[PDB]
Each structure stands twice: as C-alpha cells, then as structure tokens.
Length: 123
Length: 324
Ligand SMILES: *[C@@H]1O[C@H](CO)[C@@H](O)[C@H](O)[C@H]1NC(C)=O
Ligand SMILES: *[C@@H]1O[C@H](CO)[C@@H](O)[C@H](O)[C@H]1NC(C)=O
Ligand SMILES: *[C@@H]1O[C@H](CO)[C@@H](O)[C@H](O)[C@H]1NC(C)=O
Ligand SMILES: [Ca+2]
Image (cartoon, rainbow over all chains, first blue to last red; front, side):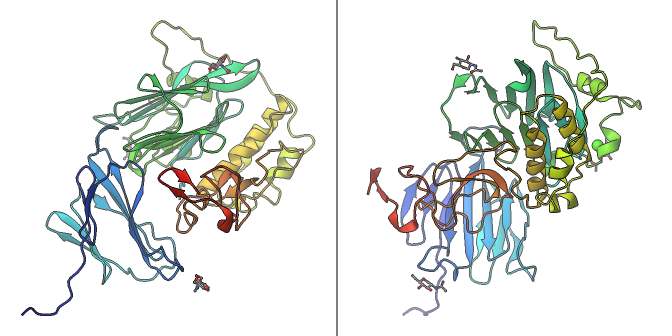
C-alpha cells in the first residue's frame, strides 16, 4: 500500500547523445544542430503553451567530439542561455518578475518554474 | 542586440571596427582582419586578402583559423581543414552554409562570419572576446576613437594602421598602398543624402551615425556608378545589427534585386523563414532583421520539394525520405 503522491516525470539527455525520454524510452542520437529537448509549443493551438528547451552539442576546445552542451530555457517571454559553465538572461518580452528561480544544487544549475525544474551538470 | 560586437569590410576598401570607427584602407595583401591575440591560448584567427577584379575591389580569400579548424574561402569554394566540402557543412559547434546571398560560417560561441562572395564581409564576435582581440576590426574595448590608433602613444593614419596589421606569405613580399590623392565628385546629385537621410533608415539615424557612410557613398560615386549601393547595403546591415528596423530602399533603379516567383526581396525580413516542415520556426526566434528572399505572410516555404513558398495546406509531407 503506497501513498498516492504524484511523482515528477523525468527526461534525461546526457553523454554523446543518449536520451531517456519522459515515458521511459531510451535511445541514442548524435546531433550537431539545435534540437528541441522539450516544448509546449506543439498543438492545435501552439500559443496556449508556455516553455521551450533547446540543446546542442558544444565542443569546448575544438570542433570535434562534443565536450559540453548549450541549453536555451525559454519561459513565455523570458529566455535563459546555459553555456560555458553558467547561465545568462536575454529577457526580451514583458519585464515582470522571473517565472523561474535559480539555484546551485551541488554540481548542478537548477532552474525551476514552479512545475518544471531543469538540472544541468554544467558540462 | 549585436550592438558593438560587429566589424565589417565593404565596397572600396571600407573597414568598420567593433566600436564604430570607419576608414578606407586600399591594401592589397593578406591582413589580420581579426585575431584573439591578448590571451594565453588563441581562439580565432580570421584573415582577409583583398584584390582586384578588373578594377572592382573584392575579397579574394578568407582564412579563418579557430580551435584547430582551418577554413579557407576563395574562388567560390570552401576548404575545410584542407579538403573541399559541399555546402552546407556542419559539425559540433561549426556550420558553414550558402544561406541567402552569402557564405556564412558560424562557430558557435566563437564567431559569425558572413562573406557576400565578392566585396562584403562581416564578423560577429562573442562578448567574452572584449579587449583580447587585435586586427583591423579593432580591440573590442568599446571605445572607438581613442585606442585603435595609438601605437606606443603615437596616433596613426588609416594607411599606417592597416599596414601594421599586415602578414606576408612565406615567399611573398607585397608592397603597401601609396596614399590616394585628393578626391572629387562628392554628392552632387544628392543621392547619398536623399537615400540615407530618407524615410527608410529613419530609426537607423537613432542608432548608427551616417556621416562616414555618407562620405563612403560619395567616394564610391567617385568610382564606378553601378557600385554606389554597397554603402547603403552596409548601412542596412549595421542598422539591422544595432537593433533598428531598416525599411525597403531598393527601387528598380537603385541597384534592383530579384528573387524567385513566390519569393520577394526584402530588407529586414525575419531570419527564420517559416517552412511547413517546421511551419512555426518563426515563433520565438531571436535574431534581428536580415535581408534576402522571403515569402508573403501566410504561405510558408516549401523546403521538401522546393516549389517556392506554398500555402500551409498544400505542401507535401515526408516519411522515411518519401515525399507525399
Ligand atoms: C485553436 O485552433 C483551432 C483549430 O485547430 C482554432 O479553431 C481556434 O480558434 C484556435 N484557438 C486559439 C485561441 O488560437
Ligand atoms: C573559380 O573556380 C572555377 C573552377 O571551379 C574557375 O574556373 C574560375 O576561374 C575561378 N574564379 C572565378 C572568379 O570564377
Ligand atoms: C582593456 O585593456 C586595456 C589594456 O591594458 C586595459 O588598460 C583596460 O583596463 C582594459 N579594460 C577593460 C574594460 O577590459
Ligand atoms: Ca578602442
């Protein structure tokens, strides 16, 4: 008999391109361009969706095998680029308070949006 | 936006540094157009060679060295690490394309190099390269008028400045351009003033000063009279890069452009052309105005069979490489 608390779905995008999607499927994909790791911007209406996450493989000292990533955490009209070891902010739209929060969780940058928490190992 | 992280080279040997300077330099050898030279380990080394096509000033060869990658663009061809490659060529962090009218080499987190193929060439650099670069594009310290032209506390002329950033071949001894005598012509008909100060670049007057561009337009008028629109094109690029919205200035007489049947030639069109393979790419883009061919609103591009811009509900689908 288990408590009936809901549990957060988990996607994992790591390594040379291994992905473990939300539904538990596993596969490997070696992509070099920018790839939508997630979004609500897919539906009969795209505009009732909120966020969007793109990633691509940075080489950190050459143009060869991948060495790190580059994340683009869009949240509504905000934006956060995760590269090179820390974050940025290119907020362009309406300038309200952040719909996100930023934290240094161990060896991770963790960015929350009250229902959607992204953890980046910084590499 | 790309406020002061841009340098450019256009028309009759006109060089614009990161911080806003403009000067003419009629060099004709290889030059260090920009280079990471105030760091323990260099990240980029982009060089230009400027030559003559009959009489037209052109760029004949670019050699971008970055992070162990060598990229030699010349003769309408691209050499990647010594091997010819067919456009577009993409790898982790690097992509080179024939996008639009140009050849664009983007080395992600390093640089963005546009090369129109004959005369123009534009560099976008990361903000982290401030104060650590040196070359015709300047130092990227943000101060235009004070720090590019002081070689050990002495002020130089643009001829001397461009001659400092010179680099001979292993077996080549290229001379220096002797100073051009006085000019003539100026803007007698007023075309440069009428266009540049006209309606199109109105808000561009609020971001980029046109004085040097007016002078360059007049100087190009002194040259051939089918080649005065290079300065207007460059001003459009710069105004778009600062953030402002350039407006269409081209008229069937002012260097007319042509595009395919369903594609219109626009100044300041959205860079991410929606195409029913990804018909909503242009939703949350971040990139300023870009010139080129575009589609009338509503009918996204058809990149699946290249039938021009097509209505959303009449363009094919793709399954496993099969067209439907
Ligand atoms: C959502 O899409 C449907 C068609 O699928 C359309 O009829 C409706 O107006 C759209 N709603 C909004 C808010 O865009
Ligand atoms: C460019 O290369 C072609 C061969 O690919 C050659 O015929 C031509 O002379 C070269 N130069 C120009 C300006 O086309
Ligand atoms: C830029 O570099 C010069 C060279 O010595 C230095 O004096 C200056 O403090 C630097 N400024 C910035 C903002 O990097
Ligand atoms: Ca300076």
